[PDB]
Length: 106
Ligand SMILES: [Cl-]
Ligand SMILES: [Cl-]
Ligand SMILES: [Cs+]
Ligand SMILES: [Cs+]
Image (cartoon, rainbow, N blue to C red; front, side, top):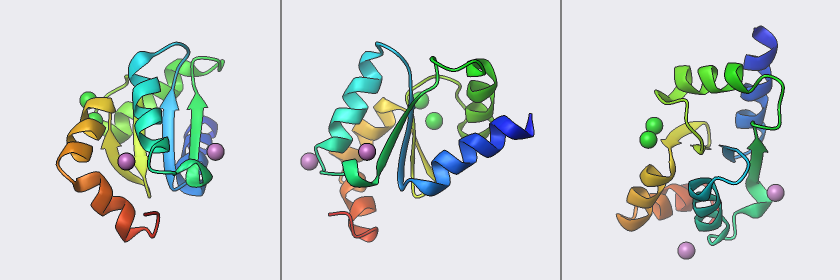
């Protein structure tokens, strides 16, 4: 499905911070909260892919892009951050702040 791929692409391309999530997922909530803690909401988009008729196709494409089909899936300026654990590693080790500094976001 070219349509699903184009739709995922547009979310990733038109939002500097793009997070694919689902309903009631604690690691989604945690990752989104960490990012909003950097005052990123203005350049953030969160897409709930569970409330979507094509959830499986979206997940398969996110796996083609990142190696995993699980949510949350996190992109920053089209670069793959990964999941919440990856975000936590980047945050604790200073990489997340460096990332955001280079984008003018902090
Ligand atoms: Cl990953
Ligand atoms: Cl992961
Ligand atoms: Cs912070
Ligand atoms: Cs937003």
